[PDB]
Every structure is written in structure tokens, then in C-alpha cells.
Image (cartoon, rainbow, N blue to C red; front, side, top):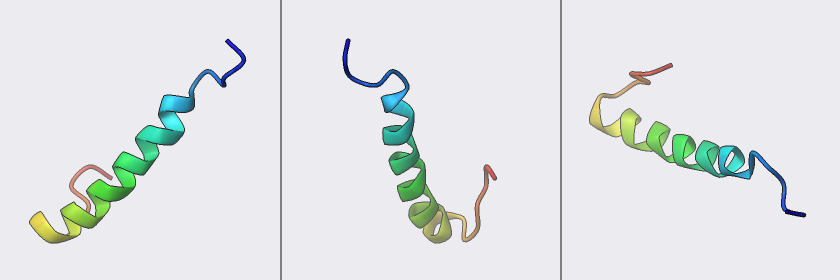
Length: 33
């Protein structure tokens, strides 16, 4: 309850940030954005 509400977002972003590192490797650039 006291916790924030969209906290997953801020945590998701971290995931997305990692995907950037992977993408730059797998495809080379950002396939989504």
C-alpha cells in the first residue's frame, strides 16, 4: 500500500535498458525504438 504504484515501470525500464545492450548485440541497433 505505502509502496509506489507504477514501481514495476521503473523496474521494467531497467529491463528495457538491458534489452538495449542485447539488441545492440543481437540485431545491432534498437529494433523496437
